[PDB]
Amino acid sequence: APSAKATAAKKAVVKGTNGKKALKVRTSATFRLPKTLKLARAPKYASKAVPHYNRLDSYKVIEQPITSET
Amino acid sequence: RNLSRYVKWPEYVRVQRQKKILSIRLKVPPTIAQFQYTLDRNT
């Protein structure tokens, strides 16, 4: 005989019925990097801890009027 | 059509799958391969 029932039962007791696979469709020829988590910085310290001030304020921009004839 | 056998997998994946294939297909000493005459489950 084949004893297909009983060799299924053999396979059951010896492996424990965890015996199939979830086959995944995979269609792309190329596999790519999964898109994952990307934080932004939370520094324990600032880089320089003091903002530099307005470099380019107006009183510093405008140096001079010209006083020439043209 | 699903072409799962045709894809270009990544490299380390290729390594480990080929490795298992290779360790299957290789003749072995008896010292190792007393491993995998290993234990069954209910015990």
Image (cartoon, rainbow, N blue to C red):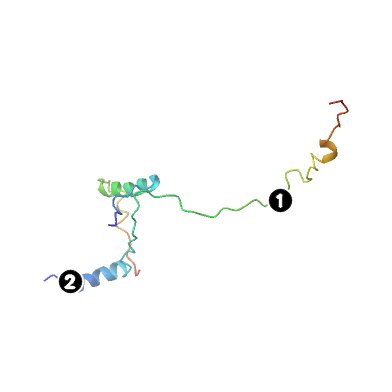
SS label for mark 2: helix
- Sequence-wise, which precedes: disc 2 or disc 1? 2
Q: Residue at x 34, y 64 (%)?
A: A22
Quadrant in which residue B15 is drawn: top left
Q: Residue at x 29, y 51 (%)?
A: B33
- Residue A10 higher or lower than B13, as above or below: below
Q: What label sits on residue A44 in the rendered view?
A: 1
Q: What's under tag 1, amino acid-wise?
A: Lys
Quadrant in which residue A48 is drawn: top right
Crowd rating for badge 2 (residues with CA inside 10 Å; few <14, some 14–19, many 20+): few
Q: Between residues A12 and B15, which one lies in front from this camera angle?
A: B15
- As drawn, is A46 to the left or to the right of A57? left
- As drawn, is B4 to the left or to the right of A54? left
Q: Residue at x 82, y 40 (%)?
A: A58
What residue did someone put label 2 on?
A: A4
Query: Residue B28's spot in the image, x, y percent?
Result: 27, 46
Identify the subunit bearing mark 2. A
